[PDB]
Image 1 (cartoon, rainbow, N blue to C red):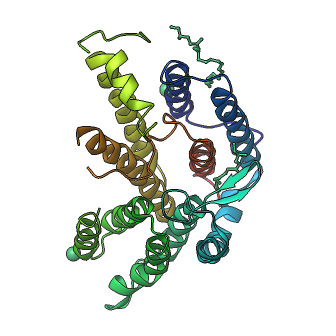
Image 2 (image 1 turned 60 degrees about the horizontal axis):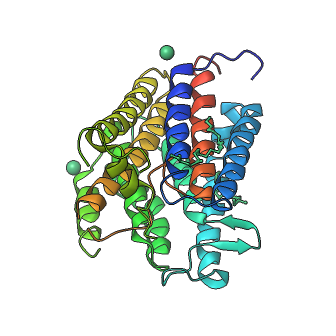
Length: 299
Ligand SMILES: CCCCCCCC/C=C/CCCCCCCC(=O)OC[C@H](O)CO
Ligand SMILES: [Cl-]
Ligand SMILES: [Cl-]
């Protein structure tokens, strides 16, 4: 953490998408008190992503299995002592504190699957079972809320990890598509409510150049993630980085089809749409990915 050998390009990409999100929220249905909550979320997010830099990658992958278990027990616990919002209890609300176990599940499952899938030889049966028995508790506890947007993100991440690894992945796509079935000019206005109340306003006030630029920022972000992914000697790191990039790109392309018209899910546009927990969790995951990239040439 003392040396700062990071990929600063990815840092600039995250910062650029975040600054666009903030300058849009200030015109996309603004409110004096609704911009403060997300500003405090950004502060918390940067702070948490910095705190996680005092963590070696050895320790991070040592926590691969405990974090997975804790996300499983927290997914189970949110079903009992959660708060209903849109018909599903998926949030822990302790006054000003809002923590959804879906994010912890995503990171824990990515770490657990990456670590358990770096031994090249496996028995001819566990190529199906190991990702199955590690993903099914998470997806099942995500459907008991019910929240299938996070279930889709999780399952598609697992698909990406398995596919990049070199294991049976067709059954995962079958499960993914089956679960997914039960669901103003070139210039714009320039600043002149549903979940998409941050993106439906941006797409109209900034038009084709705005959407093209934002999708370009997301394309460059996914490109830099997959470039950092194949730039890691360890296989577990390759898997972890690629799973993260998959989940992120998948939320983005889910919001695309939502805007086209899908049904809608609770999945926000990462770093861009309104939501303090999603911002904080995306920043924390990006901090993890940044620290595993900085420790890529170490033991
Ligand atoms: C790393 C990136 C950090 C990003 C920066 C941290 C956030 C700070 C936000 C301050 C208020 C800005 C709110 C948005 C600005 C516009 C608000 C406004 O006055 O709306 C009027 C409208 O734009 C007239 O056309
Ligand atoms: Cl660069
Ligand atoms: Cl297959």
